[PDB]
Image (cartoon, rainbow over all chains, first blue to last red; front, side, top):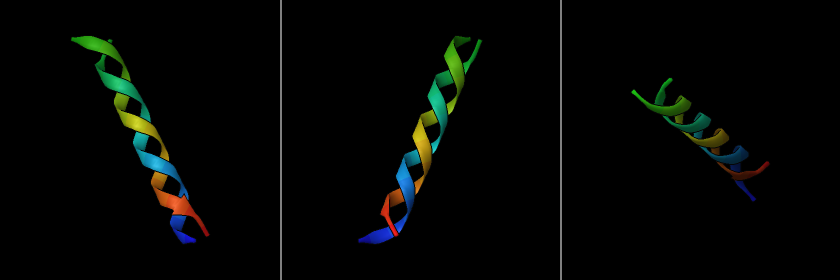
Length: 16
Length: 16
């Protein structure tokens, strides 16, 4: 279903 | 900034 695996790109929110 | 790396969890939207 949909495309890819999961939701968004990466892990969490930001960079740090 | 924030926490983690990127936005969300995974790659794209769904599973497939």
